[PDB]
C-alpha cells in the first residue's frame, strides 16, 4: 500500500461513495458544475480580505477577465503574484480557486491577480497559454509592481511554466522573480510509475486525464504543451510542489530535476500522504491547510530574497 | 567566459599571482600550514560568541577532538548541528572552519559541534567516515538535543551525505532532521563538464583534486566514497548548495536531482559567480558573507518546520 494521511483516506472514502455520473461521463457544462459543488462542500470560504476587484483587460482574442486580491492596498510597489487556476484546461474559473487566492494574498502579503483564461473545448489549445501570457504581460505593464511571481495548480502549473519560458525568451516590462507550479502537468505522456500506481482511486484518474486531454487537443510537440522537452536554463527560482499520491507526481519530480540540472535554484516540496487537487479541498482535508501555508511561507522567503538582492 | 562576481575575480587575481609552491608540491604538513595561513588572511575572525568548549570524545580508534559552539547556552533541548570540515580528507581542522561554525551558531541559534576526524594519508579511507559516524552517534547519545542537523563542506559535504545514509539505515538515539552539504564531493570520477570548465584558475584545481584523491585512497565502489551510485530514498530534507565556478558543481547538481527523483524534499541553491571554498573566504570575498547568511537562513526555516512536526 502507499502512505496516506488519515484525513486524506477519510475524504477518499467519501469521494468513492458518491452516486451519480463520473466527471468523464459528463459534457463540459455538467463537469464545470460538479467542480463548483465540490468546492462549496470541501473548500474553506474566502474569509476576510481588504480588497477584491474584478475587471476586464484587453487580450488578443477578446477581453480577459481578471480578479485582484489585496489584503493591504496601501502597500508600496513590490512583487505581484499572477495565478492560473487548474481544471485540466476545461473546468475551473475565478470562483473555484477564490478561497486559495485569498489565502495566498493574506499569507504572501502581495497582491494576487487571478486570470480567467479561455477554456476547452470551446477554445482548444493554444487559447489558454495565449490568454495567460497576454494577461501576465498586461500585469507587468499596467500594475504597480517590481516583479512577477507566477503560480498555478495542475493545468495551471503547466501554464505557470510555459508562461515563464515565453517571458524568459521575450521579457515583460518587469522580470519574473519566482515561479510556484503546484502539482503541474509538464508532459502529455503517461509512462510514469506514479501513473501506474495512482491512476485510480485518487481523485485524478486515468479516465479524467484522458477526458481533459481530448478536449484541450494540445499539440504534443509544442513547448506550450510539453515543456519538459525544452531547455530550462535561465528560468527564475522555482518552488515546485507535488502530492505523493498523484499520478502526476513523477513528471513533477522529473521537471524539478531538470531545473536543477540546468542550474536553476529550485525548492522541491512533496506533500506526503496527500492527493492531487488538495489546494481546493482545505475543508474536506484539513491537513491541506498546513500544506498551503507551508509552501507559501517558503515562497514568501524566496521572493524576499530576490527583492533584497 | 562564465559569469564571475567582480569581487571573486579580484580575489582570484590575487591568488593566481601568489609565488611559492602549489599545495600539491607540498607534503601534508606543509599543505596543512598553507590552509591555516590562507584562512588567517582571507577569513573573517570568530567574532563574539557566548560559549566555545573543546573536548575529546571516545572514538573507534582513539580520542576524537570536538569543539562545541553555542551563542545561547541557557537554551532548552532543541536541534544540534554536527559539522564536518572540508580539505580533501587531508587538510583542515577545528581552526580552519572556526569562523564559519561560530557564524552558523549565531545565525541558526542552535549549538554547533565541529568534529576533527582522522586525516589521510596517515589514516586513509575509510577512517574519516567511520570517525564522523562515531562522533555523530556520540552526540546523539550524550548532548541534550531533540534531533541532529548534519552539515559540512566539500569532503565534509561528502561526509554529511555518507553519515546521513548510515544513520538512515541504523538510527542514532535521535533522528536526523535535516542535512546541509555545501559544495559536496559525491563521486571519485571526473567526467563532468564543470571539471573540464573550471579545473584551473578557480582555487580547487585538477592537480589539487588528484593529490587529495591519491592520499585518501577511496574505494570507488564503496557507498562511503561514492554516494551518487546508491539509493537516496528516505534521507531527510536536504539543502544542497553548489558554487557555479566549481569543478564539483555538476556532481552536486546531479546528487540534488537524484534526491528529488527519490522523493526527498530538497532545496538546491547555487552561489552564482563564485568559487569552491567560499565559506572560508568571507574577508577576501566579501560577497561570501551573503552566501553564508542566505543559506543558513534557509536552513533555519527548514529546521523550524521539522520541529513544528
Image (cartoon, coloured by chain):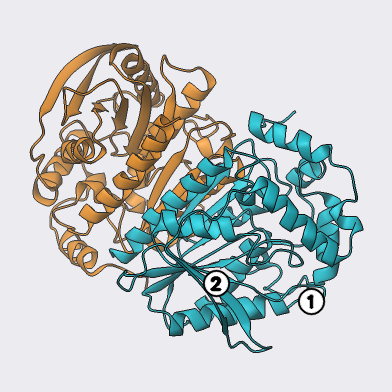
Chain colours: A cyan, B orange
- Residue B153 falls in which quadrant of the image? top left
> Which residue is at 39% across, 49% downward?
B241
Dot 2 alpha-carbon crowd within 10 angstroms: few under 14, some 14 to 19, many 20 or more: many
Q: Secondary structure at mark 1?
A: loop
Whether pointer 1 and pointer 2 mark residues with C-beta atoms closer than 8 Å, the reply is: no
> Which residue is at 73% across, 67% downward?
A89
Query: Residue A82, percent across and down?
Result: 51, 69
Q: Is residue B27 visible?
A: no
Dot 1 alpha-carbon crowd within 10 angstroms: few under 14, some 14 to 19, many 20 or more: some
Image quadrant containing the N terminus of chain B:
bottom left
Residues at marks 1 and 2, common chain? yes
Chain of the residue that carries numbered disc 2 in the rendered image: A
Q: Nearer the viewer, residue B73 or B237?
A: B73
Please, is residue A21 above or below residue B234 in the view? Answer: below
> Which numbered disc covers residue A124?
1
In this rendering, would A269 be left or right of B94? right
Name the residue that disc number 2 marks: A67
Please, is residue B126 above or below residue B210 in the view? Answer: above
Query: Residue B166, percent across and down?
Result: 48, 23
> Which residue is at 39% across, 33% downward?
B160
- Residue B94 falls in which quadrant of the image? top left
Query: Residue A148, percent across and down?
Result: 45, 71
- Residue A85 falls in which quadrant of the image? bottom right
Callout in the foreground (1, 2): 2
In this rendering, would A167 be left or right of B275? right
In this rendering, would A231 be left or right of A72? right
Amino acid at each position: 500500500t502507499h502512505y496516506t494521511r488519515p484525513d486524506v483516506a477519510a475524504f477518499l472514502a467519501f469521494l468513492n461513495a458518491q452516486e451519480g455520473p463520473k466527471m468523464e461521463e459528463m459534457p463540459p457544462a455538467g463537469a464545470r458544475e460538479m467542480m463548483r459543488v465540490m468546492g462549496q462542500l470541501a473548500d474553506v470560504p474566502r474569509g476576510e480580505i481588504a480588497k477584491v476587484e474584478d475587471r476586464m483587460i484587453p487580450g488578443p482574442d477578446g477581453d480577459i477577465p481578471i480578479r485582484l486580491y489585496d489584503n493591504r492596498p496601501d502597500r508600496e510597489a513590490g512583487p505581484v503574484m499572477v495565478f492560473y487556476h487548474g481544471g485540466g484546461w476545461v473546468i475551473g474559473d475565478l470562483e473555484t480557486h477564490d478561497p486559495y487566492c485569498a489565502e495566498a494574498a493574506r499569507i504572501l502579503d502581495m497582491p494576487v491577480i487571478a486570470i480567467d483564461y479561455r477554456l476547452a473545448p470551446e477554445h482548444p489549445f493554444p487559447a489558454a497559454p495565449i490568454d495567460c501570457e497576454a494577461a501576465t504581460r498586461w500585469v507587468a505593464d499596467n500594475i504597480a509592481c517590481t516583479g512577477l511571481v507566477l503560480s498555478g495548480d495542475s493545468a495551471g502549473g503547466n501554464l505557470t511554466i510555459v508562461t515563464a519560458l515565453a517571458l524568459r525568451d521575450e521579457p515583460a516590462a518587469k522580470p519574473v522573480i519566482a515561479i510556484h507550479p503546484i502539482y503541474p502537468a509538464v508532459t502529455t505522456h503517461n509512462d510514469w510509475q506514479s501513473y501506474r500506481d495512482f491512476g485510480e482511486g485518487h481523485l485524478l484518474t486515468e479516465g479524467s486525464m484522458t477526458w481533459f486531454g481530448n478536449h484541450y487537443a494540445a499539440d504534443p510537440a509544442d513547448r506550450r504543451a510539453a515543456p519538459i522537452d525544452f531547455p530550462a536554463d535561465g528560468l527564475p527560482p522555482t518552488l515546485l510542489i507535488t502530492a505523493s499520491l498523484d499520478p502526476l507526481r513523477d513528471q513533477g519530480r522529473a521537471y524539478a530535476a531538470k531545473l536543477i540540472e540546468a542550474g536553476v535554484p529550485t525548492t522541491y516540496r512533496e506533500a506526503k500522504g496527500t492527493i492531487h487537487g488538495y489546494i481546493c479541498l482545505a475543508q474536506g482535508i484539513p491537513s491541506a491547510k498546513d500544506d498551503i501555508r507551508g509552501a507559501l511561507t517558503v515562497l514568501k522567503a524566496i521572493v524576499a530574497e530576490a527583492t533584497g538582492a
